[PDB]
Length: 415
Ligand SMILES: NC(=O)CC[C@H](N)C(=O)O
Image 1 (cartoon, rainbow, N blue to C red):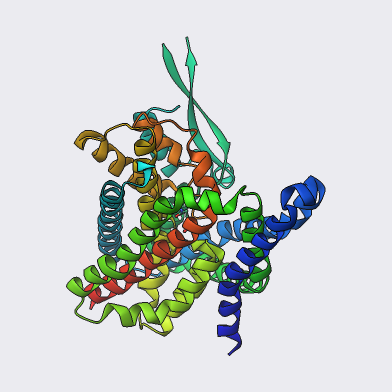
Image 2 (image 1 turned 135 degrees about the vertical axis):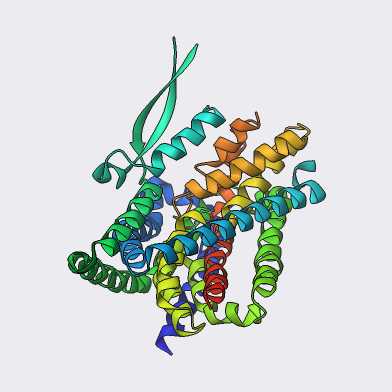
């Protein structure tokens, strides 16, 4: 089956990239290649990242506009409220699990204010300019006059603000009635034409993933020794992801929906494999919607409203990764964590996951926020960036999975 062959190649691309990067790192690696050859060697991964980032804006905007315009305003409100509750609860559970695992295994045994960060999140939720929000996000810095906070739009897509605007605009189109049907059709057609482009990009995805992983483990120095140093951190992250995706989320699905959760997960295994490969939830969004609608029988209006929102707001993997990283860095620096600091870590990780952009390496940009909020040093992030390519991929799975089951849950609530 060609459809399964594509995903098999996408997954095997990670293994092939690991092998290629280990082979290149041996026999000199970066020093033997030199910057001129290093850039060319790593370029295909960068090209894949560029394509994935390009598709996100139209894909998310059109999908959300259509999904919101496809539901009654009251039904949409109830569904969105329950979906937000599910996302928040699952993210909090992931954060708590990560903190507990980090405190039990102790992987470390071997600046912006928090209020300003939350106000920046609120500002990004309501973009000041729709065109600017497509490639910029509000961010607060300080002038020492007393540190007075002054904000500006820095680079980085404001995907959360565009998501909110898309939902509101879809609701407005629904309320318009016959007059909004033309725009609903326009945005559905744009969404489908974007699904076509995503499907085409998925064919380049294997080569891009291979070269991305190979470059990211060639850039790593002393791969064996660095893995020996970060083994416990990697174990904590992957074990937390496994527990959350295989025990916690299916347990919630079973409790709220007596149907077997693992059959639902098998129904989307292919989207999960694509998410592990590309490490981007948005690239899996088309295939995930297809699988939940076709394999799991989730209604079209539930799926195409929930999954696009969850791909940006619901990131359980990101929250677990950030909590584990925070506790690991605190242990490295020998700072004890109390209930106040643990709760701060949990809340800040939830907010950061909500603010994350859902792109490869998109979860490390906001870990510094947690480290600053807990008064932990920010330099240690240098270590985490080395392992990201692996951990991030795991996160993506637990991210996209968190969406799918949620839809499967909410649909069952509708019935
Ligand atoms: N570490 C993370 O979860 C970042 C986001 C993740 N790469 C995704 O797109 O789902």
